[PDB]
Image (cartoon, coloured by chain):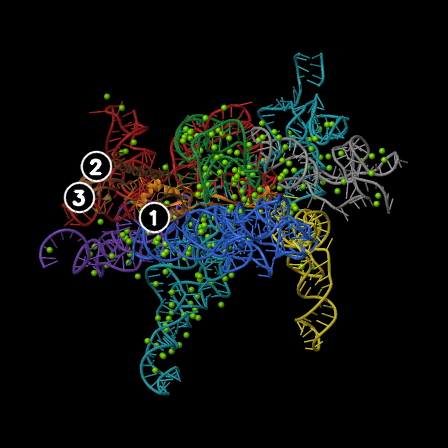
Chain colours: A brown, B orange, C yellow, E blue, F purple, G cyan, H green, I red
Amino acid sequence: MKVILLEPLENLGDVGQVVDVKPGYARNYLLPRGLAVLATESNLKALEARIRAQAKRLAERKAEAERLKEILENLTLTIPVRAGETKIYGSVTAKDIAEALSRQHGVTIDPKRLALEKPIKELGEYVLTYKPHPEVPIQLKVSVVA
Amino acid sequence: SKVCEISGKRPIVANSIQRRGKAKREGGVGKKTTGISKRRQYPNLQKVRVRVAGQEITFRVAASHIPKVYELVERAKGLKLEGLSPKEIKKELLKLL
RNA sequence: GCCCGGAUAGCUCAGGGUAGAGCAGGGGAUUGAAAAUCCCCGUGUCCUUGGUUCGAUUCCGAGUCCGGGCACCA
RNA sequence: GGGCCUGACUGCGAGGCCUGCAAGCCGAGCAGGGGCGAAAGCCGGGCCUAGUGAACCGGUGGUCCCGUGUGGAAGGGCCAU
RNA sequence: UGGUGUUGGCUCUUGGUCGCGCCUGCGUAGGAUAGGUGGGAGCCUGUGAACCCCCGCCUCCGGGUGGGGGGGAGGCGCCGGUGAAAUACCACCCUGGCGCGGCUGGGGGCCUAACCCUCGGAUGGGGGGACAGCGCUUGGCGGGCAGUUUGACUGGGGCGGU
RNA sequence: CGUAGGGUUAGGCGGGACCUAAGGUGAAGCCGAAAGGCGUAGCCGAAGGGCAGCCGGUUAAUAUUCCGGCCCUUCCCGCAG
RNA sequence: GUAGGGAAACCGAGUCCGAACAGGGCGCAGCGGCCGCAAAGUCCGCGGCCGUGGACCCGAAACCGGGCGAGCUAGCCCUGGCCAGGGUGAAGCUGGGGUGAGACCCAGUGGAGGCCCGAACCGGUGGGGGAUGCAAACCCCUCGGAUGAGCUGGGGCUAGGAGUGAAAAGCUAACCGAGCCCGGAGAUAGCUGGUUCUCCCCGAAAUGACUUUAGGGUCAGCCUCAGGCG
RNA sequence: UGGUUCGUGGAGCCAUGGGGGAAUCUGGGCGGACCACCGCCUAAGGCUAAGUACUCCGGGUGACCGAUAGCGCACCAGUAC
RNA sequence: AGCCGGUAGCGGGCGUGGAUCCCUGGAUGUCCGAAUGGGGGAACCCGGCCGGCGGGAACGCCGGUCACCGCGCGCGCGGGGGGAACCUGGGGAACUGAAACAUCUCAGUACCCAGAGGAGAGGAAAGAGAAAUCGACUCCCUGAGUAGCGGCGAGCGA
Ligand SMILES: [Mg+2]
Ligand SMILES: [Mg+2]
Ligand SMILES: [Mg+2]
Ligand SMILES: [Mg+2]
Ligand SMILES: [Mg+2]
Ligand SMILES: [Mg+2]
Ligand SMILES: [Mg+2]
Ligand SMILES: [Mg+2]
Ligand SMILES: [Mg+2]
Ligand SMILES: [Mg+2]
Ligand SMILES: [Mg+2]
Ligand SMILES: [Mg+2]
Ligand SMILES: [Mg+2]
Ligand SMILES: [Mg+2]
Ligand SMILES: [Mg+2]
Ligand SMILES: [Mg+2]
Ligand SMILES: [Mg+2]
Ligand SMILES: [Mg+2]
Ligand SMILES: [Mg+2]
Ligand SMILES: [Mg+2]
Ligand SMILES: [Mg+2]
Ligand SMILES: [Mg+2]
Ligand SMILES: [Mg+2]
Ligand SMILES: [Mg+2]
Ligand SMILES: [Mg+2]
Ligand SMILES: [Mg+2]
Ligand SMILES: [Mg+2]
Ligand SMILES: [Mg+2]
Ligand SMILES: [Mg+2]
Ligand SMILES: [Mg+2]
Ligand SMILES: [Mg+2]
Ligand SMILES: [Mg+2]
Ligand SMILES: [Mg+2]
Ligand SMILES: [Mg+2]
Ligand SMILES: [Mg+2]
Ligand SMILES: [Mg+2]
Ligand SMILES: [Mg+2]
Ligand SMILES: [Mg+2]
Ligand SMILES: [Mg+2]
Ligand SMILES: [Mg+2]
Ligand SMILES: [Mg+2]
Ligand SMILES: [Mg+2]
Ligand SMILES: [Mg+2]
Ligand SMILES: [Mg+2]
Ligand SMILES: [Mg+2]
Ligand SMILES: [Mg+2]
Ligand SMILES: [Mg+2]
Ligand SMILES: [Mg+2]
Ligand SMILES: [Mg+2]
Ligand SMILES: [Mg+2]
Ligand SMILES: [Mg+2]
Ligand SMILES: [Mg+2]
Ligand SMILES: [Mg+2]
Ligand SMILES: [Mg+2]
Ligand SMILES: [Mg+2]
Ligand SMILES: [Mg+2]
Ligand SMILES: [Mg+2]
Ligand SMILES: [Mg+2]
Ligand SMILES: [Mg+2]
Ligand SMILES: [Mg+2]
Ligand SMILES: [Mg+2]
Ligand SMILES: [Mg+2]
Ligand SMILES: [Mg+2]
Ligand SMILES: [Mg+2]
Ligand SMILES: [Mg+2]
Ligand SMILES: [Mg+2]
Ligand SMILES: [Mg+2]
Ligand SMILES: [Mg+2]
Ligand SMILES: [Mg+2]
Ligand SMILES: [Mg+2]
Ligand SMILES: [Mg+2]
Ligand SMILES: [Mg+2]
Ligand SMILES: [Mg+2]
Ligand SMILES: [Mg+2]
Ligand SMILES: [Mg+2]
Ligand SMILES: [Mg+2]
Ligand SMILES: [Mg+2]
Ligand SMILES: [Mg+2]
Ligand SMILES: [Mg+2]
Ligand SMILES: [Mg+2]
Ligand SMILES: [Mg+2]
Ligand SMILES: [Mg+2]
Ligand SMILES: [Mg+2]
Ligand SMILES: [Mg+2]
Ligand SMILES: [Mg+2]
Ligand SMILES: [Mg+2]
Ligand SMILES: [Mg+2]
Ligand SMILES: [Mg+2]
Ligand SMILES: [Mg+2]
Ligand SMILES: [Mg+2]
Ligand SMILES: [Mg+2]
Ligand SMILES: [Mg+2]
Ligand SMILES: [Mg+2]
Ligand SMILES: [Mg+2]
Ligand SMILES: [Mg+2]
Ligand SMILES: [Mg+2]
Ligand SMILES: [Mg+2]
Ligand SMILES: [Mg+2]
Ligand SMILES: [Mg+2]
Ligand SMILES: [Mg+2]
Ligand SMILES: [Mg+2]
Ligand SMILES: [Mg+2]
Ligand SMILES: [Mg+2]
Ligand SMILES: [Mg+2]
Ligand SMILES: [Mg+2]
Ligand SMILES: [Mg+2]
Ligand SMILES: [Mg+2]
Ligand SMILES: [Mg+2]
Ligand SMILES: [Mg+2]
Ligand SMILES: [Mg+2]
Ligand SMILES: [Mg+2]
Ligand SMILES: [Mg+2]
Ligand SMILES: [Mg+2]
Ligand SMILES: [Mg+2]
Ligand SMILES: [Mg+2]
Ligand SMILES: [Mg+2]
Ligand SMILES: [Mg+2]
Ligand SMILES: [Mg+2]
Ligand SMILES: [Mg+2]
Ligand SMILES: [Mg+2]
Ligand SMILES: [Mg+2]
Ligand SMILES: [Mg+2]
Ligand SMILES: [Mg+2]
Ligand SMILES: [Mg+2]
Ligand SMILES: [Mg+2]
Ligand SMILES: [Mg+2]
Ligand SMILES: [Mg+2]
Ligand SMILES: [Mg+2]
Ligand SMILES: [Mg+2]
Ligand SMILES: [Mg+2]
Ligand SMILES: [Mg+2]
Ligand SMILES: [Mg+2]
Ligand SMILES: [Mg+2]
Ligand SMILES: [Mg+2]
Ligand SMILES: [Mg+2]
Ligand SMILES: [Mg+2]
Ligand SMILES: [Mg+2]
Ligand SMILES: [Mg+2]
Ligand SMILES: [Mg+2]
Ligand SMILES: [Mg+2]
Ligand SMILES: [Mg+2]
Ligand SMILES: [Mg+2]
Ligand SMILES: [Mg+2]
Ligand SMILES: [Mg+2]
Ligand SMILES: [Mg+2]
Ligand SMILES: [Mg+2]
Ligand SMILES: [Mg+2]
Ligand SMILES: [Mg+2]
Ligand SMILES: [Mg+2]
Ligand SMILES: [Mg+2]
Ligand SMILES: [Mg+2]
Ligand SMILES: [Mg+2]
Ligand SMILES: [Mg+2]
Ligand SMILES: [Mg+2]
Ligand SMILES: [Mg+2]
Ligand SMILES: [Mg+2]
Ligand SMILES: [Mg+2]
Ligand SMILES: [Mg+2]
Ligand SMILES: [Mg+2]
Ligand SMILES: [Mg+2]
Ligand SMILES: [Mg+2]
Ligand SMILES: [Mg+2]
Ligand SMILES: [Mg+2]
Ligand SMILES: [Mg+2]
Ligand SMILES: [Mg+2]
Ligand SMILES: [Mg+2]
Ligand SMILES: [Mg+2]
Ligand SMILES: [Mg+2]
Ligand SMILES: [Mg+2]
Ligand SMILES: [Mg+2]
Ligand SMILES: [Mg+2]
Ligand SMILES: [Mg+2]
Ligand SMILES: [Mg+2]
Ligand SMILES: [Mg+2]
Ligand SMILES: [Mg+2]
Ligand SMILES: [Mg+2]
Ligand SMILES: [Mg+2]
Ligand SMILES: [Mg+2]
Ligand SMILES: [Mg+2]
Ligand SMILES: [Mg+2]
Ligand SMILES: [Mg+2]
Ligand SMILES: [Mg+2]
Ligand SMILES: [Mg+2]
Ligand SMILES: [Mg+2]
Ligand SMILES: [Mg+2]
Ligand SMILES: [Mg+2]
Ligand SMILES: [Mg+2]
Ligand SMILES: [Mg+2]
Ligand SMILES: [Mg+2]
Ligand SMILES: [Mg+2]
Ligand SMILES: [Mg+2]
Ligand SMILES: [Mg+2]
Ligand SMILES: [Mg+2]
Ligand SMILES: [Mg+2]
Ligand SMILES: [Mg+2]
Ligand SMILES: [Mg+2]
Ligand SMILES: [Mg+2]
Ligand SMILES: [Mg+2]
Ligand SMILES: [Mg+2]
Ligand SMILES: [Mg+2]
Ligand SMILES: [Mg+2]
Ligand SMILES: [Mg+2]
Ligand SMILES: [Mg+2]
Ligand SMILES: [Mg+2]
Ligand SMILES: [Mg+2]
Ligand SMILES: [Mg+2]
Ligand SMILES: [Mg+2]
Ligand SMILES: [Mg+2]
Ligand SMILES: [Mg+2]
Ligand SMILES: [Mg+2]
Ligand SMILES: [Mg+2]
Ligand SMILES: [Mg+2]
Ligand SMILES: [Mg+2]
Ligand SMILES: [Mg+2]
Ligand SMILES: [Mg+2]
Ligand SMILES: [Mg+2]
Ligand SMILES: [Mg+2]
Ligand SMILES: [Mg+2]
Ligand SMILES: [Mg+2]
Ligand SMILES: [Mg+2]
Ligand SMILES: [Mg+2]
Ligand SMILES: [Mg+2]
Ligand SMILES: [Mg+2]
Ligand SMILES: [Mg+2]
Ligand SMILES: [Mg+2]
Ligand SMILES: [Mg+2]
Ligand SMILES: [Mg+2]
Ligand SMILES: [Mg+2]
Ligand SMILES: [Mg+2]
Ligand SMILES: [Mg+2]
Ligand SMILES: [Mg+2]
Ligand SMILES: [Mg+2]
Ligand SMILES: [Mg+2]
Ligand SMILES: [Mg+2]
Ligand SMILES: [Mg+2]
Ligand SMILES: [Mg+2]
Ligand SMILES: [Mg+2]
Ligand SMILES: [Mg+2]
Ligand SMILES: [Mg+2]
Ligand SMILES: [Mg+2]
Ligand SMILES: [Mg+2]
Ligand SMILES: [Mg+2]
Ligand SMILES: [Mg+2]
Ligand SMILES: [Mg+2]
């Protein structure tokens, strides 16, 4: 009796998988405990629907990512600070690079998704990895200046 | 045993035919009937307890049509059944037949 | 009528290259006998018949004979 | 008693005996292929009268007659047992 | 009372078939533990050889072999001696033994959720538990019950006889 | 016996508007081809529980029933505590 | 009906068995002078007899279905009621004796018991009577039980292959080895009985064979009618 | 196992109590085991007059009865008993 | 043109201003009965609610309403019971016949039960069955005592 697992189960399968079990195991255990639902034609389609939407709403987040990748790697964010030869008096932070990115180029960004351990204290050119989406990193060249 | 609530399978009358001798197709003289008496064949009726709409419903059903019960449960989700007695829930399932 | 056993010494039983074993039988040791015991000895187409092998009790085919087993009977 | 042999035939059968029926009995002669005999001829078991069992059901060997739209098959029939 | 349905999870141990893999096979004559035929003058070894240490082993107790730590130019064949049957390496197969794998099947152990019992409380707890009960089917016991049969001749019937 | 007329009077007697017994019936629930069979509560069910009337007089015919004397019960409403 | 033979394929005045042109089985063909009469056959009516039906009529003991019954009787359930009077005198208790303490003994009190006697009540032992009865079980005399496994009123439950039974196959509405009513139903009866106006002609058999047959049947024998032969 | 003429028969077909369990026309059932070929038909949802049966009722008519007959009942009969 | 039932009589009435009487529709219709507010030993007994009658609160009477079940959304609609035969479905004997009896027969009859209606069933091919054909079903004739079925018996029978 084929059923659709609603949870991952020990040596049966992964959630969403369609496995074949003895009718009794399904009626008297799996189905009443919500661990699975019998693989009817009626909800076979329901599985095909949510796989089709999930991978859709996944790849759209990939395209929302590639949109900010094509843009942000294709420019430099320039930060005027006050400094003496090398050392900045204050510091530029993610919050700083944030408010900077909109005011200059009209794009919003998330400080927390940006890779900066210690706040930037030296003048120069930096490359800062950005992740609005795993496996889709955005390199950002940033120029801090006087 | 009585009647399947799903299929309407029902006890039937059959004969119990006692035979002796060797079948002709085995080189025998032939079968002789040494007794015919009436008897009944009952449906393989069983109990099926399912939880529907938060109520417990029991079916007396032939084993053959046991899956037909769980299907009625699936066909039932589109119905508005809460507040109902188990008796009234069962009635709704059986009209989905 | 079909399946499954057999046949090996006097009696009963063991088994691709042996023909065995026990008990019956005979002498010998031994004894109040009657035994128990102990030593030695015999008793084979391994049913027949046909072929396999290099040869065969075996393997096979075939009948003969006795067994067991199941079914049937107008 | 011995020699050669298988007629302890196949296909029929005039005419009778007996007889409630059904059975039972005897049978010359013709054809096929034989045996014995020089031949005439004899041989369809046994000097004779007991040694037996209708039909139904079914087995087996033939026959190739029927074969459920058709060709086959299934299963029957027929001859023999 | 077998099969099967209702009837499920996890283990353990067996049996049988099929496929592959590897080995086993000792009367004698003889190099020794020679399966059957067949191919065959060459196979192997640096893609590790003659002994050594570990053991799966099976031994008919002489031996056979398997994996492993030894181990750094070598072992057996055709040669041939007696063989019915030659010894190397391959190859289909026979008698077995296992190692997996396929499908079957038998036991045992546990589990809980079907089903059963129970708990003043119950979508729950406890116990039994895939047994039991019940359906279909198998064969058996079965005067408890049922339908019947249980001859005729005959110096009456029975008995005897036929 | 035939025809006709007359005769049986209750808050307190008996039964019901009270209670339950066996049993019967039976919302729940269970079972059975049909008919039906069960079944907790509940309901029904008495000669058992419970409950307020004694004596006399009267009629052709009834009387703890009518009458007389002396008693009592329940229900409704009211007043008081 | 007009064609039959063969198990059949099939042939056909023939066909089957067979190797046969053999042999056999079962089959095949009007009176008058083209008119006429007759006829195969077939159709209707009438009569005899047969088959199927209850089949000439009456009659079982029984079998089956569905119902009706425990107001009789049997057991049980619930709830009530009844058992004059007299007799016997268990245990226990008290006192006394007893002994180390006891057992135990005596007296008194006590009132037990499927105890005794005997009415009611329940029975039914022997005899007599009755015998178209007073009575489809009674009457008289006698006799058993009578505090118990007792008797009895009312209310209930259990039934037909079923109940109930201190057990007799007893009882279940006056006949119970399987109740009663209606139904299957006109069961079946190879048995017994019965079978109705007249006259005329003929006129048997009681044997044989076979028969779960023997007092019943089939065939033959023997009777009768019609047509034919002579 | 039932139905049909079909009693296990060569036993199909229709139905179905139990087990196993498809497909959507290039799908499926049938033509008497089975197979090939050739044909027939579209299962697992339902409805549908009329032609047919019967006679409590009414009328019409009898080579139907005529009071022991005809209905059990001609009548105060499903009565009396 | 007579009339007040069978039914006369006593005693009283009606009708050509159309009676009695016949047909149709309507009104009334105690109580019981499917019986249905509840109970019950049918034709009796005891209640709730609203309204009315009495002097009426107790008591009583009158009118309306109040069972259970099914189905649709407390309101509705329907069901229940009967009917001589006839009909369909679910169950289903035995005597008897086989001159015994068991398979077979009687017979899917008798009977029980559910349901139905003036009928009921059946009915528009997953048919038939050999016709290269037919064309729903029902009913009658015939096919035919054929084909077949059968302790190949008795019989059964498309
Ligand atoms: Mg800052
Ligand atoms: Mg059976
Ligand atoms: Mg054969
Ligand atoms: Mg038979
Ligand atoms: Mg038979
Ligand atoms: Mg029968
Ligand atoms: Mg039975
Ligand atoms: Mg279950
Ligand atoms: Mg559940
Ligand atoms: Mg099924
Ligand atoms: Mg199934
Ligand atoms: Mg043989
Ligand atoms: Mg022996
Ligand atoms: Mg011997
Ligand atoms: Mg000689
Ligand atoms: Mg001679
Ligand atoms: Mg010669
Ligand atoms: Mg002759
Ligand atoms: Mg003769
Ligand atoms: Mg003779
Ligand atoms: Mg002769
Ligand atoms: Mg000659
Ligand atoms: Mg010559
Ligand atoms: Mg000559
Ligand atoms: Mg001759
Ligand atoms: Mg014979
Ligand atoms: Mg016979
Ligand atoms: Mg035959
Ligand atoms: Mg043959
Ligand atoms: Mg042919
Ligand atoms: Mg065919
Ligand atoms: Mg054919
Ligand atoms: Mg062909
Ligand atoms: Mg042909
Ligand atoms: Mg043949
Ligand atoms: Mg044959
Ligand atoms: Mg043949
Ligand atoms: Mg013959
Ligand atoms: Mg069983
Ligand atoms: Mg199982
Ligand atoms: Mg366990
Ligand atoms: Mg355990
Ligand atoms: Mg636990
Ligand atoms: Mg549990
Ligand atoms: Mg649990
Ligand atoms: Mg529980
Ligand atoms: Mg539990
Ligand atoms: Mg547990
Ligand atoms: Mg089980
Ligand atoms: Mg089986
Ligand atoms: Mg059995
Ligand atoms: Mg008996
Ligand atoms: Mg017996
Ligand atoms: Mg028994
Ligand atoms: Mg006999
Ligand atoms: Mg006799
Ligand atoms: Mg005699
Ligand atoms: Mg005598
Ligand atoms: Mg005599
Ligand atoms: Mg005499
Ligand atoms: Mg005499
Ligand atoms: Mg005798
Ligand atoms: Mg008087
Ligand atoms: Mg009076
Ligand atoms: Mg008074
Ligand atoms: Mg009142
Ligand atoms: Mg009362
Ligand atoms: Mg009460
Ligand atoms: Mg109810
Ligand atoms: Mg009822
Ligand atoms: Mg009822
Ligand atoms: Mg009841
Ligand atoms: Mg009760
Ligand atoms: Mg009350
Ligand atoms: Mg009552
Ligand atoms: Mg009462
Ligand atoms: Mg009282
Ligand atoms: Mg009391
Ligand atoms: Mg009282
Ligand atoms: Mg009183
Ligand atoms: Mg007083
Ligand atoms: Mg007085
Ligand atoms: Mg008086
Ligand atoms: Mg007074
Ligand atoms: Mg006050
Ligand atoms: Mg013919
Ligand atoms: Mg010929
Ligand atoms: Mg000729
Ligand atoms: Mg001829
Ligand atoms: Mg006559
Ligand atoms: Mg005649
Ligand atoms: Mg009759
Ligand atoms: Mg008749
Ligand atoms: Mg007659
Ligand atoms: Mg009988
Ligand atoms: Mg009998
Ligand atoms: Mg009865
Ligand atoms: Mg009584
Ligand atoms: Mg009484
Ligand atoms: Mg008392
Ligand atoms: Mg007394
Ligand atoms: Mg006294
Ligand atoms: Mg006394
Ligand atoms: Mg005295
Ligand atoms: Mg006394
Ligand atoms: Mg005295
Ligand atoms: Mg005294
Ligand atoms: Mg005392
Ligand atoms: Mg003392
Ligand atoms: Mg004393
Ligand atoms: Mg006393
Ligand atoms: Mg005294
Ligand atoms: Mg006494
Ligand atoms: Mg005395
Ligand atoms: Mg006395
Ligand atoms: Mg008495
Ligand atoms: Mg007496
Ligand atoms: Mg006396
Ligand atoms: Mg007397
Ligand atoms: Mg007398
Ligand atoms: Mg008398
Ligand atoms: Mg007396
Ligand atoms: Mg007296
Ligand atoms: Mg006296
Ligand atoms: Mg006395
Ligand atoms: Mg006395
Ligand atoms: Mg006494
Ligand atoms: Mg006494
Ligand atoms: Mg007394
Ligand atoms: Mg007592
Ligand atoms: Mg009493
Ligand atoms: Mg009493
Ligand atoms: Mg009584
Ligand atoms: Mg009882
Ligand atoms: Mg009873
Ligand atoms: Mg009764
Ligand atoms: Mg009876
Ligand atoms: Mg009866
Ligand atoms: Mg008996
Ligand atoms: Mg009994
Ligand atoms: Mg008694
Ligand atoms: Mg009676
Ligand atoms: Mg009586
Ligand atoms: Mg009696
Ligand atoms: Mg008697
Ligand atoms: Mg008696
Ligand atoms: Mg009887
Ligand atoms: Mg009887
Ligand atoms: Mg009797
Ligand atoms: Mg009686
Ligand atoms: Mg009677
Ligand atoms: Mg009746
Ligand atoms: Mg009747
Ligand atoms: Mg009859
Ligand atoms: Mg009669
Ligand atoms: Mg008889
Ligand atoms: Mg007779
Ligand atoms: Mg008579
Ligand atoms: Mg006479
Ligand atoms: Mg004459
Ligand atoms: Mg004369
Ligand atoms: Mg004679
Ligand atoms: Mg005679
Ligand atoms: Mg005989
Ligand atoms: Mg006899
Ligand atoms: Mg005799
Ligand atoms: Mg006799
Ligand atoms: Mg006789
Ligand atoms: Mg005669
Ligand atoms: Mg004569
Ligand atoms: Mg004559
Ligand atoms: Mg005549
Ligand atoms: Mg004449
Ligand atoms: Mg049939
Ligand atoms: Mg059949
Ligand atoms: Mg049949
Ligand atoms: Mg068939
Ligand atoms: Mg077919
Ligand atoms: Mg089929
Ligand atoms: Mg089928
Ligand atoms: Mg099925
Ligand atoms: Mg197609
Ligand atoms: Mg297809
Ligand atoms: Mg089909
Ligand atoms: Mg067809
Ligand atoms: Mg078709
Ligand atoms: Mg269609
Ligand atoms: Mg259809
Ligand atoms: Mg219709
Ligand atoms: Mg019609
Ligand atoms: Mg009429
Ligand atoms: Mg009339
Ligand atoms: Mg008269
Ligand atoms: Mg009359
Ligand atoms: Mg007269
Ligand atoms: Mg008359
Ligand atoms: Mg009438
Ligand atoms: Mg009348
Ligand atoms: Mg009469
Ligand atoms: Mg009369
Ligand atoms: Mg009368
Ligand atoms: Mg007047
Ligand atoms: Mg006057
Ligand atoms: Mg007058
Ligand atoms: Mg005028
Ligand atoms: Mg007018
Ligand atoms: Mg009117
Ligand atoms: Mg009422
Ligand atoms: Mg009532
Ligand atoms: Mg009021
Ligand atoms: Mg007043
Ligand atoms: Mg008032
Ligand atoms: Mg009132
Ligand atoms: Mg009033
Ligand atoms: Mg009212
Ligand atoms: Mg009714
Ligand atoms: Mg109706
Ligand atoms: Mg009918
Ligand atoms: Mg029917
Ligand atoms: Mg019927
Ligand atoms: Mg029966
Ligand atoms: Mg019978
Ligand atoms: Mg009989
Ligand atoms: Mg008959
Ligand atoms: Mg008979
Ligand atoms: Mg007879
Ligand atoms: Mg008999
Ligand atoms: Mg019979
Ligand atoms: Mg039968
Ligand atoms: Mg009959
Ligand atoms: Mg029948
Ligand atoms: Mg009838
Ligand atoms: Mg009509
Ligand atoms: Mg119609
Ligand atoms: Mg259509
Ligand atoms: Mg048709
Ligand atoms: Mg066409
Ligand atoms: Mg068409
Ligand atoms: Mg014809
Ligand atoms: Mg028949
Ligand atoms: Mg038939
Ligand atoms: Mg038949
Ligand atoms: Mg029949
Ligand atoms: Mg038919």
User: Do tags 1 and 3 sit on the same chain?
Assistant: yes
The residue lying toward the viewer, choosing from F16 and C6, is C6
Ligand 1 is within 8 Å of the C-beta of the residue at disc 2: no
| Amino acid marked by disc 3 | Glu
Which image quarter has ligand 101?
bottom left
Which quadrant, please, contains the C terminus of chain A? top left
Report the chain holding disc 3: A
Instruction: Give the secondary structure at mark 3.
Output: loop
What label does residue A85 carry, if any?
3
Residue occupied by mark 2: A107
Q: Splitting the image into 4 quarters, where does residue H7 fall?
A: top right
Residue positioned 60% across, 43% down in the render = B26
Measure how far apart labels 1 and 3 are at the Cα level. Answer: 69 Å
Q: Earlier in the sequence, mark 3 or mark 2?
A: 3
Residue I127 drawn at (x, y percent): 49, 30
The residue lying toward the viewer, choosing from A104 and A46, is A104
Q: Earlier in the sequence, mark 2 or mark 1?
A: 1
- Does residue B49 appear anywhere in the picture? no
Select label 2 or label 1 by which is in front. 2
User: Do tags 3 and 2 sit on the same chain?
Assistant: yes
Residue occupied by mark 1: A33
Residue E110 drawn at (x, y percent): 40, 57
Q: Earlier in the sequence, mark 1 or mark 3?
A: 1
Residue E41 drawn at (x, y percent): 61, 44
The residue lying toward the viewer, choosing from I158 and A142, is A142
| Amino acid marked by disc 2 | Val
The residue lying toward the viewer, choosing from C39 and B84, is C39
Pointer 3 local density, CA inside 10 Å: few below 14, some 14–19, many at least 20: few
Report the chain holding disc 1: A
Instruction: Give the secondary structure at mark 2.
Output: loop
